[PDB]
Image (tube, rainbow, N blue to C red; front, side, top):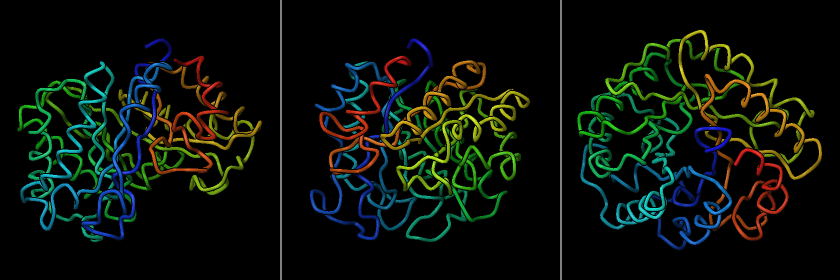
Length: 305
């Protein structure tokens, strides 16, 4: 694995067009291309995070049965990643919400997670990610949803796999200590919780501009999260990060990762946002062979692979 336990990319597309449910495959959304994943594997990446919509995988009620077609494509994508030996993160890219309403039933969420984990229980290279970027919702609820997900996953017999938990405030690293302290209390009989945090480098942290605040902004924005993980005996991962293809952002990216590399007692690695087949000229596209980050950023990341 060289520098970090995990270093890789998001593989985005199956969650596209979230205003259109169920939406239409090939029109509103698309699954990752196994051939370009293989290229990224060949460059040394060993983790691929796969966003999908909860409502497309389990329509109508989260306690119901899966949609066969969307599930079949999730299964195929996971197997393409893991058959080679890399890790696949199963990411319900749902912001703590289901049909655009806050998930307020931990029991219902636990049933959803038993359903999903049952599909992958024997695969130790699957990582379950409780939900992408909880935000603007009750802090105790976020804790309880993460715990319910863990309980559902382990109840399915999926005991070998790591579980990525996410906090409130869009799971931002720079905001973590201000809001997410209660997340320290999560329990897991397999002792494989990783605290996933996200971090962008533009002024407001939204990850929507190619301009970075400064050449040190990434390393600055993760220092207090690093100390929190260490003080509480936890492990973390950066599950979503990017910067534009310019000198300032390239320096900020390297400085962030160099800082994480001297703090591997807590940091397990990082996952770029994003590859996937429908990004075109996106400022952060890691998609081989022509994404701008694949061409201009990947060369600066090779030291960590």
